[PDB]
Image 1: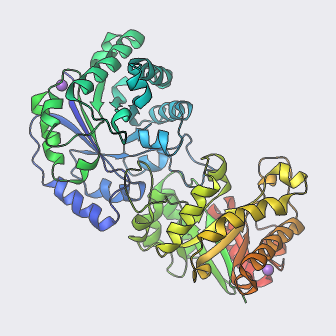
Image 2: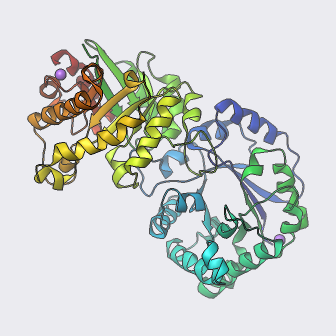
Image 3: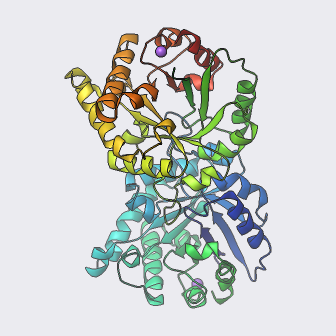
Length: 251
Length: 251
Ligand code: NA
Ligand code: NA
């Protein structure tokens, strides 16, 4: 039995440390039902306050890290810096960084390798764009991303890896994803793991749905056999986040 | 008389919050001579501790910011977040971000516009690469960068703008820059400002040397008529930083 996993990705929000602290206080009072692993990802500059104030049964995550321990990389934040605060998680490969910030698969593989080799746990994001979706080539595209990922995972570190599927074809495109879509692609990913690295690893790795998750669809999505949780966007800034965390009882 | 200006760019250093706090304590005990404006730029995740612990007669700076107030930009830090801590400065356009992180001039112009329109002061970086240097086309190249910058500066905000010249042709290239080189390019920049936006603005804007600045060359460089200070790299992590700040007495 894989522990249900819910990551709250604040993205570049909120605007002020005051709003962040109010948000934390909200999360600290939330009543979690069932068995669920909860992680909260926030902007770098809010990480210290999050680590300090967030309920200790949840974990803090970065939204990105660089490839090196330190050095001449103006503007970048590195794994050692994050760890020095006691922070154990980072998101990698989010579609927004792949797209807006031009992060390619080689950059991302290097990050996953460095992060894991340095004691961190990763939420690794993948997902196909509209054209591959419409061509019926989603599985091929996603497979290539996972294959670029796999060689970065050090032996014995798959327990520290969580994979999130983003239906990029449904983000800002005029298309929406169904519950069945989410299940199908999470299954696609799991089968890729089983074929490439073995059933034992495939059965243990949490695969999350990273599309639009809201209180109105989290229960239905949670029930999908291959969906082990969510990487939540907007709802993670709202009270609806606890409903999403509690969707685990339908999984 | 332009106030001498020294920015300490920690870049992606140090590795741990503990090292950062020790570094701050060092800077807090430093005896500054003369008249000099001091700014210290650190990784996002260290900004809160810096803002809190750094001597109040110096100012804290980000090493980068995004183009938007907030939103779906996983991994990015924004102007409002930084300001919510009382932080007033950011570096923009550093060669390492232009090169490694692929930031282009349009991205950078947008950042300068947004930052300044939102109450922040900027250290805007420019500088030509080896090929333009060797072709004797440095001034042409740098002019293009400044021209892309100028339309972003809102009326009445040139007092909030500092420009740093990076001899990228001398960074990781096997070539070294002389004191005369620094002076020549700082002058080039000032003349570009005078021609494009007027002598009054050109006479007020601080132009910094962003090449290799160390205790062994800061006095000589400081004396250069058009060099109003430095954006310091490695030395800003060392005790030699105070020598650099104190070089102002030779300007
Ligand atoms: Na499930
Ligand atoms: Na001078």
